[PDB]
Figure 1 (cartoon, chains in turn brown, green):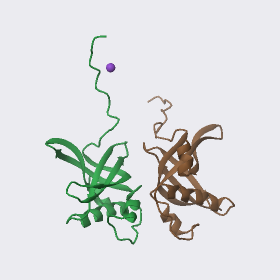
Figure 2 (spheres, chains in turn green, red):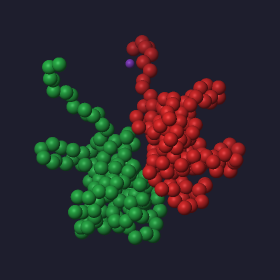
Figure 3 (tube, rainbow over the protein chains, first blue to last red):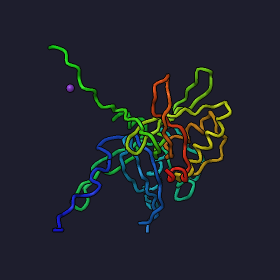
Length: 128
Length: 130
Ligand SMILES: [K+]
């Protein structure tokens, strides 16, 4: 057969549209950049797919996890008295928790994506 | 203008087809039956945006086993089951939310008319068999 540039595969994977969304942290995976990381897979109400990298070791680590925990808290889950950080308690705790999320567009290397940027509180979600 | 019947629209409420599906427990709602049994109503969202429901009834002989089946399915989708007494309580209500499961849809009869209904929660093995 004469070669013919094939059509792009998985063009119709559901991604989040711009704005705020009620989502679930469907999955959590361990990763490494040097930096220790949790990869958070996010699932939308219409099976939209997004990801968020929680990076440990830096200055924003504590705050970034707090917002996640507050968003979980505001989706009707009690935050226990655990030492939250790069540990197994946290890894397990984040799996299958409802959240509010913010989705903005993000340029990288020419093309544009829809990136999950922040985890929102009840108040910040209701604003939008 | 003279009347012409508009074509049937699409159900934005797309129901589950028959057979087996992977889904997530999207929502849990506190209810009470007509008899007076406490109930959890589980909204299930399939991978193709299908939407079904399930009534977990407490205070009968089928309650304890029904939870095992749900909690086993949650366990096999990679979530550790905590050390709590499961029942009509905050800890159960909160835990079930947001969890991936395997379900089995079948034909049932509501007031005589047939409908697609979520019947069982499958372990990993059972899912693959289908
Ligand atoms: K029409």
